[PDB]
Amino acid sequence: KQKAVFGIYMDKDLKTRLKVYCAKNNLQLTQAIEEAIKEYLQKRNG
Amino acid sequence: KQKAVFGIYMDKDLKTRLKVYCAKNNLQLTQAIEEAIKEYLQKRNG
């Protein structure tokens, strides 16, 4: 629930793929990034 | 290589966990997000 902001320069096709993912699941772009980066740390290490 | 910008409000601990991941691997925050969101789409569907 504690929030922060993030302003980065990421690739288009990749961010946009996820954008389409957010369109398909009607998800929020942010929510998807957070899920992405969340399941990424656990899939990796942290 | 085609770049875009992204400005969202994501959780702290989560984004910050990844920040520590970027500190540990000396990675770039953005590069980590992109890897995160990349491996997320493929782990999911797209």
Image (cartoon, coloured by chain):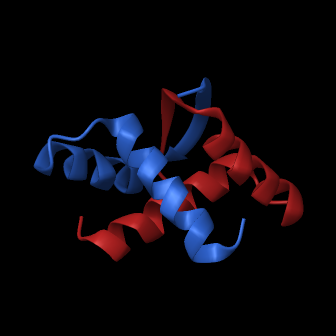
Chain colours: A blue, B red
How many numbered circles does the render carry?
Answer: 0
Give percent across and percent down for residue B37: 46, 58
Looking at the picture, does residue B16 appear above or below residue B38? above
Give percent across and percent down for residue B29: 71, 48
Q: Residue furthest front?
A: A1
A14 with respect to B36 (left or right):
left
B21 with respect to B24 (left or right):
left
Looking at the picture, does residue B8 appear above or below residue B31? above
Compare residues A45 and B26 and report the one nearer the observer.
Answer: A45
Give percent across and percent down for residue A44: 63, 75
Looking at the picture, does residue A28 appear above or below residue A32? above
Looking at the picture, does residue A1 appear above or below residue B22? above
| Residue at the image point whose x is 40% and y is 36% from the top | A30
A30 with respect to A1 (left or right):
left
Compare residues A9 and A36 and report the one nearer the observer.
Answer: A36
| Residue at the image point whose x is 49% and y is 64% from the top | A39
| Residue at the image point whose x is 76% and y is 47% from the top | B19
Question: Where the C terminus of chain B falls, by quadrant?
Answer: bottom left
Give percent across and percent down for residue B5: 50, 33
| Residue at the image point whose x is 29% and y is 35% from the top | A28
